[PDB]
């Protein structure tokens, strides 16, 4: 029917600008509403202030309980049928130096840790969710002698490692150097014993792919993976040694607008999508002015979902039961309300 | 020569004309008639004419009343990938099969039909009567020519005889060539192209041991001598240009062209010699095979890094059986494949165009004017046309340019893909033409009805890859404690390497409505028309003429396609010429023209969802041209001025409604009639007699008056005429020889740059919002060449002809030809950083020898 416009929630200033140019070129088929944080963003979605956004596994879980549903998945593979075939997602991994000692999954206690950010999927949710059953309480400041968890209390032992000066030290955002998959890996190399990151993090930051001096001489082969059974495997072996598998980023919207957003978005990708990509004098949807904006730049097409309609089926067994046993206890307000 | 319809604004060519001119190629024919352009299809073939500021399906192409397949470009595939696509080409005609072609500038719809919007091109199948004669009871002809530019050679022969009433005519033509060489200086023997190559890893943890290479027992025995992991490092290599692989490609890609044409024309003369009953069978098949060289054959650590950053490291990367180190270098392909560094990739297009037309014709002729008709004819033709794209990609050779190579166990990291897209059309046509006269009246009636179809099939779409079976495993473990190999010299990994596993997926899908959907897109339908035109002569002083025609077409499809009976398009033309003389005289012409939505435009935009068929008006055009001419001993010197209006132009876009009071787009993307633009040109030409021995002068120029949009529409782009060929002068000077038999000629074509006012435009979005766009990244710039031709018909039967084109070398790049870049061309080139690849030919020699009996 006469599907009305779709509002996109732009988490940043740049997410906003991109969303604007989009809005224009879409001739209003899509419009934007800004937000301070990803959460309240998903809230504006909740009440009808906004019609959709895309988010990682954990947030998909949160909105999932909030009653929203994933319409489409982000696909980074090159395929002749990109949209048809669903992608298996990615792997969370605990990375260590091949030259580091005796570290094993069970003996991590007392060791120094490097995390992407608190509350985020692979750097926090998965690892802390798996260790939660071991320690079965909520204080992770107690488990590791110290580490870097961006977003943790400033006097927390988990800010002890984090770099950065003044107010932004340990900050959840790039103001803090050890923030992110990247920052987490850097932390591993310079400070921590363990790093919790995705399986692409190491190759990404080694072999000269990362210009910065600390990296770039770093040999991917010099780092390995901690397997849940006590053993280790090479970085390229993450499939057979890992904590849990997260799903691809996906777009979520309220039940009613589901069909509509689904419809319009596909048109949008055929207009602005992979090819044509001429981002020079035209608008490319997946390309970004800075980094992945409203979409991972690695995005090829937005794909349908065969058997997974529901956020639980989407996230898959491995994800949950590695999490939700974690929270349980989560200080996120929206989750609490949602319960 | 002329002429069916007073006025002018058109040209004539005859078999003899063509031959004298030595035209072997579509580019040749119009090379001297400025303002007419060929429009490259990017894989090296034709794809129509550009005239009066338009091109493609905007200008008609007809043969013996049968229209020729339109330009159909299917929508772009997503993901990945690099897919075949639709040929988009328009059928090529065998000139050795034709008598005299007629070209016309401005809307011709009155005598052409649909598609005549910007102009028209009409052909004539050669007549058996070419056995002439008179006297001779039969004839035989042979043509052998050689073009240096395309290194092509063409051979045609036509044998014919007429016994009593019966008669027979057989023509066979064939050609092999390719690639149309450029000015030598276009590029020579260089550049670099870094390429990934194996080097020892240098990590201390990089050691490993492979199972099959330990004869005795286990890890602890064999470990003593570990191999070291290999890592990718590109090295700068230097090749050769023509061997290089784009971007930065200074060459036009290799092309293999081949063509075979057959013409059979029986006819029987009936009793009293008036009646003629005859039939025709034509088969012309041309093939264009090319390899896109724009596609880099090798990786390239940069590519590997890209993939590492996306998918991360791969199992076994750097590991190799025995000493074979390229074994360790492989990366993420497309369609879930790993491609080895040791092979190289190539992309090949095999494009094959087939035309097959058989029919019956009956002609009644009476003289002098007696019966209700001086000339009457019925024509029934069954024709068909097809274009077979057949894309292939392979990464299973040294490359080596190998198109046969494929994936297998022995070639662990190989890849292959095939995507074939076939677009075709068929006509079953009855048409009747009657001409009656009175003496100053000339009456003309033209009728027709046809059963037509356009069928697009998608088949032979699939992939293949072998992927090396590999495993990293851990040794027993007999001890009650287990070790995890870290790859250290003292503790290398325990690895199994094995044969490539071949797998082939089918890429064809059904009902998804995207490129990958292979359901036949078929369109069928009936169309008739009734055309009448008559001209009259008033004394010596003036001549006027006028015509009117009515067309009706209904099309059905089993899909939600945009098909509909398009409405009763009715067209007209009027013309006059005044003869106050003095050897002078004046002329005026007015005509209407139209085009129905291209079957591609009818199939719709298709975002992969359900789409509604939104009926669309035909593109409309109005042409007015006024001219003057000076007749006399010297010759006729003509000057013309024209205005063409274009309206209801079809583009992909959105509907626009107002309220609030702003604009709102609705509701779905498709092709609609969103826009109108106007052009005015000027065209001079004359041929002097000088009382050396003669010369000919032609000049043409075109300007863009205005462009405006339906204002109820949006997201429409703007027009962007890239199709108008920059104004040029053509001045020939030649000397024949009253009977002599020998002849000489010379020609000077000069073109001015290009604008750049015609390469601009706006996307025109909501409110005062729009984005500036352009058709192209650069302009062409001005150039001039001189061609020189000659011929001698020693012992006049055998006639030899020779020519040297671009006598001076004069390296230049024509814009034709660079139109292939962006501008939504039928097949778009990118990224084209160099542009040297678009250079026109240097000095080239064409040699022809004809003989007749």
Image (cartoon, coloured by chain):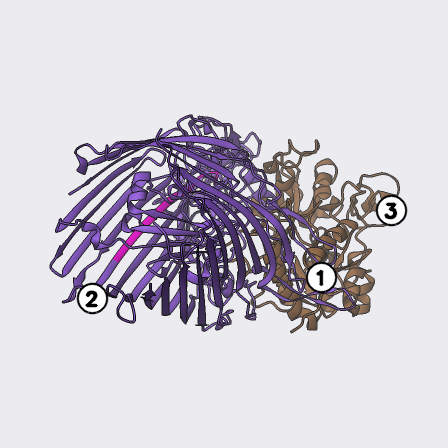
Q: Can see residue A63?
A: yes
From the image, tell me which residue sits under label 3: A154
Span shown in magenta: B282-296
From the viewer's side, name the closer residue of B515 and B586.
B586
Please state the horizontal and vertical placement of residue B78, each as a whole percent of the image: 54, 55
Please state the horizontal and vertical placement of residue B569, each as a whole percent of the image: 49, 69
**Chain in brown in the render:** A
* Circle 2/circle 3 CB separation < 8 Å: no
Report whether B15 appears left or right of B418: left
From the image, tell me which residue sits under label 1: A28
What residue is shown at x 32% (from left), y 43% (from top)?
B18
Give the mark nearest the N terminus, 3 or 1.
Answer: 1
Disc 2 element: loop
Please state the horizontal and vertical placement of residue B484, each as a whole percent of the image: 56, 43
* Circle 1/circle 2 CB separation < 8 Å: no
From the viewer's side, name the closer residue of A153 and B475.
A153
């Amino acid at each position: 029917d006469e599907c009305k416009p779709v509002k996109w929630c732009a988490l940043s200033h740049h997410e906003r600008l991109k969303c604007d140019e989009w809005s224009v070129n879409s001739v209003g088929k899509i419009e934007c509403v800004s937000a301070e944080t990803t959460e309240d963003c998903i809230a504006k979605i909740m009440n009808g202030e906004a019609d959709a956004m895309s988010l990682d596994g954990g947030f998909v879980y949160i909105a999932g309980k909030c009653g929203l549903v994933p319409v489409l998945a982000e696909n980074y593979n090159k395929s002749d049928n990109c949209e048809d075939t669903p992608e298996a997602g990615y792997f969370a991994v605990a990375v260590v130096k091949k030259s580091a000692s005796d570290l094993t999954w069970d003996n991590l206690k007392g060791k120094k840790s490097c995390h992407t950010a608190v509350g985020r999927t692979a750097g926090w949710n998965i690892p802390m969710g798996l260790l939660y059953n071991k320690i079965n309480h909520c204080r992770f400041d107690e488990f590791f002698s110290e580490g870097c968890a961006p977003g943790s209390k400033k006097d927390s032992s988990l800010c002890k490692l984090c770099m950065g000066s003044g107010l932004n030290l340990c900050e959840p955002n790039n103001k803090e150097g050890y923030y992110g998959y990247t920052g987490a890996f850097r932390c591993l190399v310079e400070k921590g014993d363990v790093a919790f990151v995705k399986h692409q993090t190491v190759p990404q930051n080694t072999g000269g792919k990362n210009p910065d001096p600390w990296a770039k001489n770093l040999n991917e082969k010099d780092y390995e993976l901690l397997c849940l059974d006590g053993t280790r495997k090479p970085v390229e072996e993450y499939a057979n040694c890992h904590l849990a598998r997260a799903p691809n980023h996906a777009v979520v919207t309220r039940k009613d607008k589901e069909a509509c957003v689904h419809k319009i978005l596909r048109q949008q990708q055929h207009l602005f999508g992979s090819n044509v990509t001429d981002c020079s004098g035209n608008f490319c949807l997946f390309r970004s002015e800075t980094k992945d904006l409203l979409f991972r730049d690695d995005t090829v097409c937005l794909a349908k979902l065969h058997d997974r309609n529901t956020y639980e089926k989407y996230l898959g067994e491995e994800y949950v039961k590695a999490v939700g046993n974690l929270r349980k206890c989560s200080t996120s307000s929206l989750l609490e309300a949602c319960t | 020569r002329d002429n069916e319809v007073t006025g002018l604004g058109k040209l004539v060519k005859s078999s003899d004309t063509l031959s004298k001119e030595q035209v072997l190629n579509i580019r040749d024919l119009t090379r001297y008639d400025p303002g007419i352009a060929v429009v490259e299809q990017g894989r090296g073939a034709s794809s129509g004419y550009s005239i009066r500021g338009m091109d493609k399906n905007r200008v008609s192409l007809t043969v013996d009343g049968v229209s020729q397949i339109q330009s159909y470009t299917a929508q772009a595939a997503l993901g990945g990938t690099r897919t075949a696509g639709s040929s988009g080409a328009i059928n090529e005609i065998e000139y050795e099969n034709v008598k005299a072609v007629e070209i016309s500038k401005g809307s011709n719809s009155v005598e052409q039909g649909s598609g005549a919007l910007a102009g028209s091109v009409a052909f004539q199948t050669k007549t058996a009567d070419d056995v002439i004669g008179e006297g001779r009871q039969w004839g035989i002809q042979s043509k052998t020519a050689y073009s240096g530019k395309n290194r092509g050679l063409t051979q045609s022969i036509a044998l014919a005889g007429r016994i009593g009433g019966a008669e027979a005519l057989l023509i066979h033509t064939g050609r092999r060539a390719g690639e149309i060489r450029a000015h030598e200086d276009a590029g020579r023997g260089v550049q670099s192209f870094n390429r990934l190559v194996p080097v020892e890893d240098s990590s201390n943890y990089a050691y490993f041991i492979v199972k099959e290479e330990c004869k005795n027992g286990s890890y602890e025995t064999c470990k003593a001598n570990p191999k070291k992991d290999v890592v990718g490092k590109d090295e700068r290599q230097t090749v050769s240009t023509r061997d290089y692989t784009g971007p930065n490609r200074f060459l036009a890609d290799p092309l293999s062209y081949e063509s075979r044409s057959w013409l059979f024309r029986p006819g029987f003369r009936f009793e009293n010699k008036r009646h003629y009953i005859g039939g025709i069978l034509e088969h012309t098949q041309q093939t264009f095979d090319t390899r896109d060289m724009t596609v880099p054959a090798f990786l390239t650590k940069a590519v590997f890094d890209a993939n590492k950053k996306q998918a991360g490291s791969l199992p076994g990367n750097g590991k190799y059986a025995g000493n074979h180190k390229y074994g360790g270098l492989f990366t993420n392909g497309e369609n879930g494949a790993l491609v080895g560094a040791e092979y190289g990739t190539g992309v090949f297009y095999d494009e094959t165009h087939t035309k097959s037309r058989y029919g019956l014709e009956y002609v009644y002729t009476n003289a002098d004017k007696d019966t209700w008709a001086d000339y009457a004819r019925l024509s029934y033709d069954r024709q068909g046309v097809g274009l077979d794209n057949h894309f292939q990609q392979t990464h299973c050779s040294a490359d080596g340019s190998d198109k046969y190579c494929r994936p297998s166990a022995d070639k662990p990291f190989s890849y292959y893909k095939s995507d074939r897209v076939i677009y075709g059309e068929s006509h079953r046509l009855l048409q009747a033409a009657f001409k009656k006269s009175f003496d100053r009246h000339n009456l003309s009636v033209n009728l027709g009805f046809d059963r037509f179809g356009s069928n697009l099939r998608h088949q032979d779409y699939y992939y293949q890859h072998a992927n090396r079976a590999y495993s990293s495993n851990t040794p027993p473990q007999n001890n009650g404690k287990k070790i995890s190999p870290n790859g250290s010299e003292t503790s290398p990994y325990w690895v199994t390497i094995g044969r490539g596993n071949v797998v082939t997926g089918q890429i064809c899908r059904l009902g998804n409505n995207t490129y990958t959907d292979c359901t036949p897109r078929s369109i069928n339908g009936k169309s008739y028309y009734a055309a009448v035109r008559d001209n009259v002569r008033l004394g010596r002083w003036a001549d006027v003429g006028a015509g009117l025609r009515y067309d009706y077409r209904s099309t059905h499809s089993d899909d939600g396609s945009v098909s509909t009976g398009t409405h009763r398009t009715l067209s007209w033309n009027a013309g006059i010429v005044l003869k106050p003389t003095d050897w002078l005289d004046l002329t005026y012409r007015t005509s209407t023209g139209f085009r129905l939505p291209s079957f591609a435009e009818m199939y719709g935009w298709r975002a992969g969802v359900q789409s509604k068929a939104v009926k669309i008006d035909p593109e409309k055009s109005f042409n007015k041209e006024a001219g003057i001419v000076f007749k006399g001993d010297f010759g006729n010197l003509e000057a013309s001025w024209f205005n063409n209006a274009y309206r209801d132009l079809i583009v992909r876009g959105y509907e626009a409604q107002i309220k609030d009071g702003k604009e709102e787009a609705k509701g779905d993307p498709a092709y609609l009639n969103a826009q109108s633009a106007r052009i005015t040109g000027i065209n001079i030409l004359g041929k002097i007699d000088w009382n050396g021995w003669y010369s000919t002068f032609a000049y043409n120029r075109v300007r863009v008056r205005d462009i405006k949009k339906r204002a109820d529409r949006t997201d429409i782009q703007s027009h962007l005429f890239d199709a108008i060929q920059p104004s040029r002068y053509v001045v020939g000077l030649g000397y024949d020889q009253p009977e002599g038999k020998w002849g000489v000629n010379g020609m000077l074509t000069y073109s001015k740059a290009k604008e750049i006012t015609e390469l601009l435009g706006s996307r025109a979005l909501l409110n005062g919002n729009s984005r500036n766009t352009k058709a192209t990244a650069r302009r062409t710039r001005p150039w001039y060449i001189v061609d020189v031709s000659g011929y001698y018909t020693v012992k006049k039967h055998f006639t030899l002809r020779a020519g040297v084109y671009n006598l001076l070398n004069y390296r230049y790049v024509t814009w034709e030809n660079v139109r292939q870049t962006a501008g939504g061309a039928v097949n778009q080139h990118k990224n084209v950083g160099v542009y040297n690849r678009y250079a026109a030919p240097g000095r080239n020699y064409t040699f022809s020898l004809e003989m007749k009996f």
